[PDB]
Image 1 (cartoon, rainbow, N blue to C red):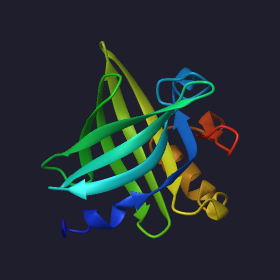
Image 2: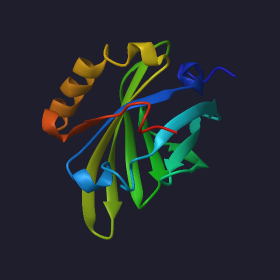
Image 3: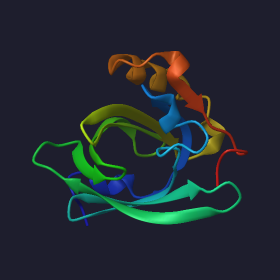
Length: 151
């Protein structure tokens, strides 16, 4: 159903790059080194299936980004509480989000770039660098992913 535009984010996506102030969150074995499979908008929430690399196999997990009164802002409960923000989106090609993670009085920032088509994996790296700079992360805090990293 139409949901103010959110429905166009549904379907298959592919993770291209991660960034964080805390490198251990996104480097090998990190809590936020997880990849998108697909999303579906329902009731104004974003429901997603993610893939968690287990070094060999991968596990598929379902999560709900709960809508809030602020648009583009969602609650996501995963390794603590996350305030999730949709930063820059073209539903036909790419999506950039970032999260403020809260885990036992510690906070971290994590950003994520996904695309519809991996042939476009270079095209939005500059856009991702720019969003990262806007939220206070530097280019050396970005991890670019490849087929060898993904599930």
